Image (cartoon, rainbow, N blue to C red):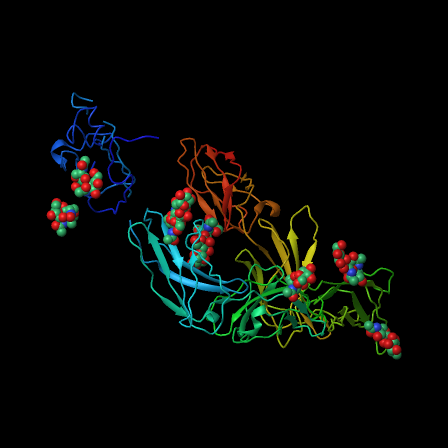
Length: 585
Ligand SMILES: *[C@@H]1O[C@H](CO)[C@@H](O[C@@H]2O[C@H](CO)[C@@H](O[C@@H]3O[C@H](CO)[C@@H](O[C@@H]4O[C@H](CO)[C@@H](O)[C@H](O)[C@@H]4O)[C@H](O)[C@@H]3O)[C@H](O)[C@H]2NC(C)=O)[C@H](O)[C@H]1NC(C)=O
Ligand SMILES: *[C@H]1O[C@H](CO)[C@@H](O[C@@H]2O[C@H](CO)[C@@H](O[C@@H]3O[C@H](CO)[C@@H](O[C@@H]4O[C@H](CO)[C@@H](O)[C@H](O)[C@@H]4O)[C@H](O)[C@@H]3O)[C@H](O)[C@H]2NC(C)=O)[C@H](O)[C@H]1NC(C)=O
Ligand SMILES: *[C@@H]1O[C@H](CO)[C@@H](O[C@@H]2O[C@H](CO)[C@@H](O[C@@H]3O[C@H](CO)[C@@H](O)[C@H](O)[C@@H]3O)[C@H](O)[C@H]2NC(C)=O)[C@H](O)[C@H]1NC(C)=O
Ligand SMILES: *[C@@H]1O[C@H](CO)[C@@H](O[C@@H]2O[C@H](CO)[C@@H](O)[C@H](O)[C@H]2NC(C)=O)[C@H](O)[C@H]1NC(C)=O
Ligand SMILES: *[C@H]1O[C@H](CO)[C@@H](O[C@@H]2O[C@H](CO)[C@@H](O)[C@H](O)[C@H]2NC(C)=O)[C@H](O)[C@H]1NC(C)=O
Ligand SMILES: *[C@H]1O[C@H](CO)[C@@H](O[C@@H]2O[C@H](CO)[C@@H](O)[C@H](O)[C@H]2NC(C)=O)[C@H](O)[C@H]1NC(C)=O
Ligand SMILES: *[C@@H]1O[C@H](CO[C@@H]2O[C@@H](C)[C@@H](O)[C@@H](O)[C@@H]2O)[C@@H](O)[C@H](O)[C@H]1NC(C)=O
């Protein structure tokens, strides 16, 4: 390496994005064998140039160029023509948003690690910059955190912290154009603890009381410097929704705690996070989660019971079909072990049974009877079911009454009036009308009381249900009542086939018959029968449904007449197959 003809000042600068650069520039002899002076030289720059009238030749050797103010990202001026013409002398590289009181600033003493402090830089400055974390005990005073380039805001001190002992922090921020500090803060670290989270967690419940399980576990290493205050969240294996638990109900350090009033025999799954008693300091992460079932606990309420009664078999004995429904794994309170019906008759004598299915189908006589189904499990023992299956002649008597049946909202409903004195359960069966589908039925039982219910199978529309409502009083079932109702209608599918009867010299009578159940897809309100001629204006009448004929009236003598008549279900109509008659002369 040798020499560089001429220098500026210096090789590098520093752009304080609003001020003036004092540049000055060709040594004593490089100016000799090239033959110029301060003159010959320009302050060029890869477009136009530091105008002539702009420079100020310092001495028989210089060329000061000052500056506007300043205006973009980099910036590279030139003290780069050899009098005769044709200087690449030296040039530089200035730079282009100073300091910035660091903002925000918090610290956390994350249990386990050392104190840790965050903040916020501000706005993209653009002159690399150095954050430093401070501190002092006024007893003494501490080393300095100095951010990591690859995370220029975080920071961890590097002394173990010392709860109870106000402490002193503030971020000192630096870059090229003037250093500053932040806004001081003063704490007692024991207020920025974030505890590990509780752990080694367990659920139990084999105390054998079916409303509760009870969790328990392990407080965090910090148990012993601060006073824990928790939140046991917990939910049902397969909810999406975490229930919490009253936080005055979990207030200070502890290692156990029983939650209660849970569904019996279910799966539950709990989890907790705790932090320092009052609330002054970050809470911690949730401990793994833990499971647990609940007691079992007797089956709570009746199974559903009824019998059906085939037209006796071997003249005397009368077979009798008992059948009952299954408790929803929730009236069950645990696996169903096996049903049990006992049977009692004529003053004094009776055998029981233990069916493990649901149709007990027994033998039986012509006395009055009375049956009793219960349902047992790994604990009990199931509240009594109860029928009266009678002496062979017990008739009707008292039926329900004022019974409607209808739909909405996409749910079929039957409601009637609460009969006479006091029925001890209704038990309404029902099924679907259609030629080409015997009658298969459904049934539900219904607590005595009630008088409106939404039947519950899987039924269909355009399809038409028959619904019977039998009430059960003391000593048997009552004269039952029955009603039809589709659940949602379509407009018939087919449509009536017309046809005349007779025909005057103007005015003839007409004839149909019924859109047959399975094609109606609904309660046929009414018939519109409309008719035109060849010149074919048309017109029409509508007809009060019940009607099967008519009497198209004042027509022409010697006319071509064409018809076609639609039938309509609330839902709407569908005209039949046009048919064409014609008066005499
Ligand atoms: C011959 O029979 C057919 C069979 O329906 C009649 O045509 C249908 O008639 C119903 C009612 O007459 C009607 O559709 C109604 O829509 C209403 C609402 O948009 C429903 O009203 C609701 O419930 C109450 C019933 O009025 C009402 O008070 C309440 O405010 C609410 O609006 C109403 O129940 C029906 O759903 C149409 O006019 C027609 N429906 C269809 C699908 O065609 C026809 O009216 C009969 N013709 C004669 C001349 O009697
Ligand atoms: C924070 O950030 C600023 C801005 O980037 C940093 O400025 C740096 O200052 C540090 C020391 O505070 C410095 O470490 C130097 O490395 C030099 C380059 O190699 C060293 O040179 C060494 O001795 C001679 C001097 O350059 C040289 O002959 C030899 O080659 C040898 O390497 C220098 O002496 C320091 O040891 C950085 O270089 C400098 N730049 C960078 C990118 O870090 C600084 O790190 C921080 N300053 C403060 C006040 O917090
Ligand atoms: C008649 O009564 C029995 C027992 O007295 C009842 O059996 C119960 O229902 C079935 C029996 O096979 C079981 O369902 C479950 O199957 C799954 C899947 O394989 C299995 O993982 C479950 O643990 C259980 O086996 C149920 O647990 C079973 N046992 C009992 C005590 O109820 C049922 O009402 C009738 N029996 C049968 C064989 O269906
Ligand atoms: C409490 O449980 C933690 C996590 O639930 C356990 O972590 C174990 O590390 C220990 C030593 O502490 C080993 O004996 C085990 O192999 C680890 N896991 C398990 C599931 O046993 C540990 O059992 C407990 N930790 C403390 C600090 O008491
Ligand atoms: C550059 O900036 C200051 C700011 O844009 C300007 O104000 C004065 O300018 C004249 C020469 O142009 C000088 O008399 C002064 O030196 C300037 N400041 C003062 C206090 O007089 C000026 O153009 C340049 N700057 C400075 C302060 O020297
Ligand atoms: C004449 O003027 C300039 C601007 O006053 C002088 O600036 C100096 O930079 C020089 C190198 O040229 C240093 O030796 C000095 O310390 C600065 N000031 C002075 C008074 O010397 C420079 O000396 C002169 N330039 C030339 C080419 O002779
Ligand atoms: C079925 O029938 C039993 C009647 O036989 C016996 O009755 C008395 C004397 C007790 O010894 C009884 O335990 C015997 O079984 C009922 O007692 C028995 O509990 C019945 N099963 C059920 C579920 O009731």
